Image (cartoon, rainbow, N blue to C red):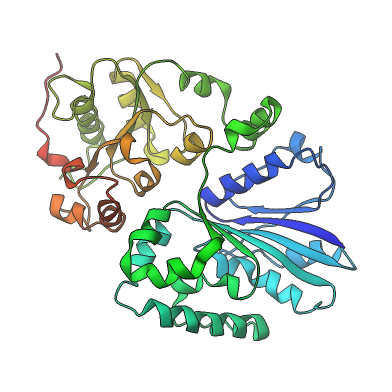
Length: 391
């Protein structure tokens, strides 16, 4: 009997957790492993160190049929150890369930480990607030066994179905926010249901491996030493989160570059409304699709250190390199940050947000406010901040 470990995720957070799982087990050079991590390319010089390592593409949050080609290489008795994105768990496991049903005597499912995509799960559960959660769980289970038996996916509550895997297999869930499940009242049937099967996502796994495995992990995540060392200086650190353009009544891109510099100045300058203090080392996390706007900010801000697109907040949290403060333009990414680290989040104008009021009704914002992670005074609409000088 062979165990085969499958690592599947179209997003980022589950993949980061699963690359950590691989890193921890990396002394084992031959354990059969199948990677379907859409955002991460494992280096050739890492791959050639392993035997029985496979790669599968995901198309619409589901591995392609090349997955069966891989499994066929393993005749005889197999048990599958599967790691999944929670939000997409139904689509992701699909081909796995289909393969199992053609080999019921040979192939079983050993364990599922599921991790949060991010804020999405929480924003989705909020939509389920006026339902009888207890009866929703019971139906989801019946519809899950029907999916296992026939392959027919039809869930009355796709969101709740993400949390019923235990009706069928051993499962361990890893949550960004266990407080949400323990404090959201409509969710109590679910909390008591998940019983011994959930845990708070751990961010300290990195601190416990060998220095070689740490290096290995930094490599898996594409974290160059240059940026890492800069994030290690012994000084207060602040990250400004950048953006592109917004509804500012102009196609003049320069205007958006100048205004973001003014928003940064509100954190950076003693005269600014959001002043963080004179002793903070400043960093910049520009929008990936920032281009030349990232260029102006970088060239017109004083000693600001740029952080490249691949080093996400999730990457910093996994390696313990998250700065002391994070502030700037709003992104759902702020959902993952510990409370003590969030300073101010500023929302620019678009179709969904035309004011602070609208900003407070943003989905991920509403759940952070419910959780006590940010106060409404930390939420700011962009044009409420004055223009600061130059000197």
